[PDB]
Image (tube, coloured by chain):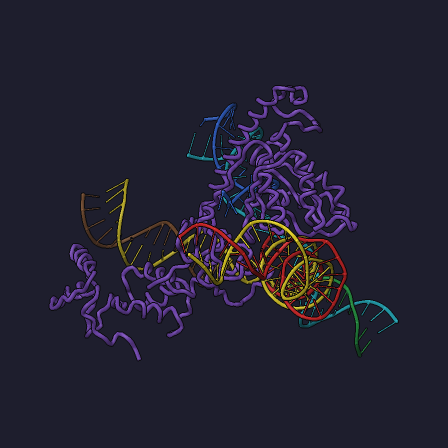
Chain colours: A purple, B yellow, C cyan, D red, E green, F blue, G brown
Amino acid sequence: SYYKSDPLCSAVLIHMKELTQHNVTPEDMSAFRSYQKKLELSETFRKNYSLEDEMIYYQDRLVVPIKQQNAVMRLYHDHTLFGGHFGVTVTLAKISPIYYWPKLQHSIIQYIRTCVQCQLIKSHRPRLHGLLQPLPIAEGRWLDISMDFVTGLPPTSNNLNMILVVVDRFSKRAHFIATRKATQLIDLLFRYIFSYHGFPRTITSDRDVRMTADKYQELTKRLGIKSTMSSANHPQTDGQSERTIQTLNRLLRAYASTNIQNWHVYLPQIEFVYNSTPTRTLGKSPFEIDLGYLPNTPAIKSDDEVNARSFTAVELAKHLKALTIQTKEQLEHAQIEMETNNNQRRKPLLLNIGDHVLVHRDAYFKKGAYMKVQQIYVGPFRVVKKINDNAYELDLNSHKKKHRVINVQFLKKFVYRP
DNA sequence: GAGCCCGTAATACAACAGATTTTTTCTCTTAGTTTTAAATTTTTATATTTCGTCGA
DNA sequence: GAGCCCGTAATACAACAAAATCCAACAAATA
DNA sequence: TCGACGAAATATAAAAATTTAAAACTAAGAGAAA
DNA sequence: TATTTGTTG
DNA sequence: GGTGTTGTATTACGGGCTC
DNA sequence: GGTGTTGTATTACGGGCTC
């Protein structure tokens, strides 16, 4: 039960094979590509096709007619003759030692994008699927605020359990919100610690139940506060707070190495140390990014001046304007530097309407659902809206899934074939 | 240089790195409880609505 | 080219990516 | 085809006196999701 | 001799 | 509307000397 | 004695044409 026991006088290679035969030319519809290929063969000298008793082949490899292309690549890709659904390299190593197939690599990668199980099972670095495209930089001071918290720490005396952080996107000002892992009184403690400065414009946070929080969201809609609400298991958007708790974790380890179970005393020292230390992407201390009144003043900084903003009373407007201008251009510099050092391999994905994208078992099933060697056979979903440049909402075929926003790091767009 | 086709063929990039239950609120869904007010009678004069009928 | 000192100063590279239970099973420690 | 009347339906304020929902109010039970 | 308790894929 | 982001050793580029 | 390692899209380099 072997193949190639069939003559085909109507295919692309007929023009190539009549270079010796010159007998019959029964071309088909859309066979004008064969005419152009024969013209290119005529103006060049690459004649290596061998014609031996109906076996027309290349120098050592069997050229296959285009009628049975899919049959051959399915035979050497599926388990009919022990393929195994591998990549283009193993498929070439199975086919190219035996067959030639002009533009074989493009045909094989097209088949990889065609075969459904390879789309659902393979990953092929599904963490580089969209550009960086960071947050818009800022406005006037204390208008954008980043919100997140680490769920659990070694508990203190039974009054405090975990640390919440507030750092603004502009100035990156540390904060010490020590919660109890909380209730609807989140707005009480949160209000007491941001309203020390004032009400922001948008909150960059995750889809956490203390902030998804239909009771708390309506408060923000009434008050005039937006909510970015980073999607399920995509904590990258929170950013400044995540980077702060990275710096806080080192600081908390430093100040509580031998002093576990009472770190709530040292937490204001943690935030004050974070506040007094200059950063890199802005080059100035977060006091200086705000009203520059580093109160410790161990020594005067470089370019010695008055450096006493307490003496200035009415002229603070020009000083804050100057700080705002230089910090805004520094934020733009940080944005472009991040975009340069990150997008060296980040391939974009821009669809925005009418596709059948997937979600490869991350933010689709539960974060608490165990990942194992169980098959990854998420069905072909649909996309109806372009919610952002780096995400697309889906019509999750479930009860509700409680969210339908999927960042591009889980999509891996499905492609059909007739 | 300058590009193009195509055919091979190198090429850095990332996955294998014990896996699962909890922890703390929240938010639909769906079955059980509780307090309370309401379906047909007398009735009494008042008035207006809407049928219902009758008359020349 | 050719290298060196020194003084700044850019520069990719990785950490924040929820936290903490055991599962199964080796061998030490008493009583 | 305009006039002429009869008559149930309500409120009404009590005392009452058996059945019927019936919608707030709890309380599992799943499903999220840092 | 059963119930522990260090560490490790 | 809504989607990364800085801390850190490490390393690259100008004044001043030998040319 | 004892300590990474390949699968995979992706991309870079020679024959043959225009020069």
Please say whether residue A127 is visible from this viewpoint.
no
Q: Whole-percent x and y of residue C25? A: 68, 72
Seen at 61% across and 19% down, the residue is A315
Residue extending farthest left: A23
Q: Whole-percent x and y of residue A49? A: 21, 65
Please say whether residue A89 is visible from this viewpoint.
yes
Number of marks in the rendered image: 0
Q: Whole-percent x and y of residue A304? A: 63, 21
In which quarter of the view is residue D5 placed?
A: bottom right
Apparent side of residue A78 relative to residue A373 in the rendered image (left or right) = left
Q: With respect to residue A255, does A300 lie above or below?
A: above
Seen at 62% across and 24% down, the residue is A302
Seen at 48% across and 41% down, the residue is A339
Q: Whole-percent x and y of residue A290? A: 62, 30
Near-viewer residue (B28 or A396): B28
Q: With respect to residue A193, does A63 lie above or below?
A: below
In which quarter of the view is residue A36 placed?
A: bottom left
Seen at 66% across and 51% down, the residue is A151
Q: Where's the C terminus of chain A, which quadrant?
A: bottom left
Apparent side of residue A288 relative to residue A81 in the rendered image (left or right) = right
Near-viewer residue (A279 or A403): A403
Q: With respect to residue A195, does A416 lie above or below?
A: below
Apparent side of residue A350 relative to residue A290 in the rendered image (left or right) = left
Near-viewer residue (A276 or A220): A220
Q: Where's the N terminus of chain A, which quadrant?
A: bottom left
